[PDB]
Length: 552
Image 1 (tube, rainbow, N blue to C red):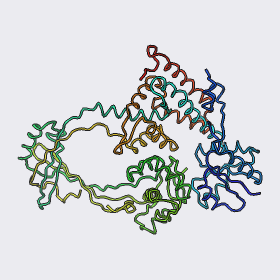
Image 2 (tube, rainbow, N blue to C red):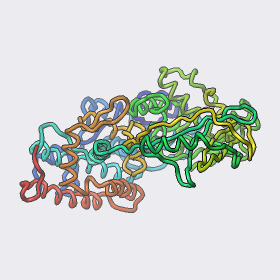
Image 3 (cartoon, helix red, strand yellow):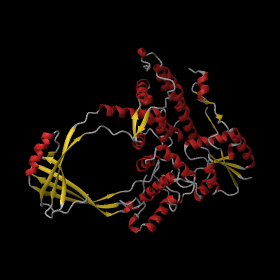
Image 4 (cartoon, rainbow, N blue to C red):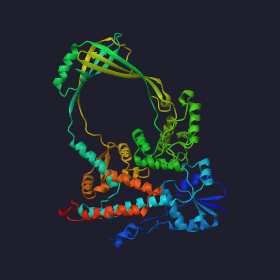
């Protein structure tokens, strides 16, 4: 009679039931239901996957999930049609595939509903228009997991043998570790270069104070490398006559950022709220399942016509016509944004302080992204003093614009060209060049994004995995490569060069994308991967004198 609707969690179940009437019975699977646990039978047994017999797999129902299978199966008969309401990503697709496979029955009896938020409208549309299970996206998800399995299960033994028991290799994890290790070595090997800067304090005809930075001497960039060059220049600057050579006023603006995507949210929540990548995604997931924000795994900065018109309505009524663009901002599945702009952080019920803060961050970025630019009247003064050229840069806020939604918060004095300035004080400053900055949780996420290595569904698992596996650590909010991280990275780089290659790893993500869009076949892709991998693994297993992996 009714329509059976399956979601992956009870939290989602509860929310979505609010928007589905009596023709539907909503049920959670309490998790994922089913999943995995030159051949060597016991290896295939362990992996659940057989690389030598065409990727044939052995899925088993997770522990405690047998009652679940019964419960769903029995519900499945009393219903005329079944709606697989899993999250929209490839993993959600595969979870839906598992539910269908286990429940059984005629395919025709199934629909796969997609939605990027759990609201009255998004739900009514998802079910009005319920499509079919996309086998390609399931295939793309299994390919990824089959290759992750393979690397984890087949490379790890080599590390136990050569290096130490209990070590774990990760196909992409090793690559992330590899970024941290390279940095460690950069920092280690850096030799700072000494250089000085001289600033001069002056006074305007008006008596106003004006600070300057020496930029040139003899029409060439100014840069003493030691105290004596600095002192020589200080003696001359002391005697020179200062005059304004040029005043460059120019209107400048600052634009608001695009709305959040998985990567930029991790960075922002880390940098602004001191939240770690894992905490952010867990809180973001709860906000999403509770119906407060759009889906947290996305890389699209797209905003729907309705989303944009409701925020413009909000800006118009709460800030005013001058904060509202003439036309909506187009920045480019949807970005992460609140589901209803009229819902404030302070009003979330099932959420705690930190998840409210993250909502507030998402809400402000969303509102700010559709507001007008901030306007500043900027000035750049170029001064002349003998053989020297000095500069001063300032700006005055003209109009706050988008910054109005953000919490509340150099102004050069007016001078004219040809104006004389009286030197008040000269202040030399010793400086040293610095090595490359350590990665923070944000810089690392940004780096994985920039290199095409991470994905919205992986960013945080990569970040957390490499730490837990003892390869790198985070202290004073920065990443440090552990010795075992360096030990494993060198071994891996030497014997599994292609596996560790950055471009090859980015290409695997695209090869996966190719499968999801029917541009490649999963098993063919798994075969290509396994062929390159086993030859690598064949060599690495030899003795060091024949090029295999070096021990200890």
